[PDB]
Amino acid sequence: ACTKNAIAQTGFNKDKYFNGDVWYVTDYLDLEPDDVPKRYCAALAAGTASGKLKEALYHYDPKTQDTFYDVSELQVESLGKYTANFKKVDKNGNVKVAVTAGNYYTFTVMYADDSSALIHTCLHKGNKDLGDVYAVLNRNKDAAAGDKVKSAVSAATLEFSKFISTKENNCAYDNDSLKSLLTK
Ligand code: HEM
């Protein structure tokens, strides 16, 4: 179960975050650590498409090869805090698993600047969830976490030393698919 009410960044700049570009997960922390693998690749695009607030997600387990994309429509709870449906799609946006009420994630932007961010998500897939997940994001897939984002981790009363890096997994991303999926 999820246990955290993540606080959104004071003065969050929504248009900069949701600009249509890609964010890579460089480091992650699940508060129920066994809920997810120890080696992971994830990225997202976030933007407004024809007036609608959207995210496109990519997950890849570098050991099993399990791969999936999702297209999400975000509803606003407050500035920087969203509830997202999700539909599982192929990389071209064709629906594999349709939207359904019980399949949603919350998404809170705790810190962001032009290059880096700290987010919280709580996934619900039916009666289950995947624990609280925190993710450090960067615009550059290879960037080590800098002082702005590490300080934000501290300000959330978390320890960056506990976060697991994605950098040693040979992660390769289809940026074109993530951008195009925003429209789907
Ligand atoms: C690097 C950090 C992350 C890890 C380790 C991770 C891990 C996972 C895993 C293992 C699943 C599959 C659960 C299952 O078997 O059903 C999953 C599903 C999912 N995750 Fe994450 N995830 C991460 C980041 C994110 C982020 C940032 C978001 C939200 C923006 C997110 C949203 C989702 C969604 C929506 C699903 C369900 C997809 C579907 O069934 O269509 N994940 N994640």
Image (cartoon, helix red, strand yellow):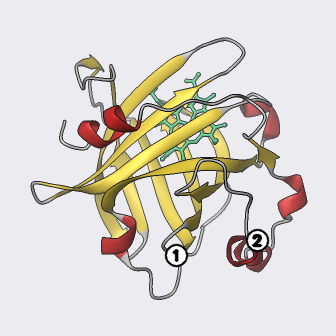
As helix, strand or loop, the secondary structure at mark 2 comes to helix
The N terminus: image quadrant: top right
* Res 33 seen here: yes
Badge number at residue 150: 2
Q: Quadrant of residue 154?
A: bottom right
Is 31 left, or right, of 176 in this rendering?
Answer: right
As helix, strand or loop, the secondary structure at mark 1 comes to loop
Look at 43% across and 71% down and name the residue there. 80
Mark 2: which amino acid? Lys
**Quick check: 153 above or below 89?**
below
Look at 31% across and 65% down and name the residue there. 76
Give whichever of 42, 95 is nearer the camera: 42
Q: Quadrant of residue 56?
A: top left
**Quick check: 83 above or below 87?**
below
Mark 1: which amino acid? Asp
Q: Please state the horizontal and vertical placement of residue 165, each as a whole percent of the image.
A: 78, 45
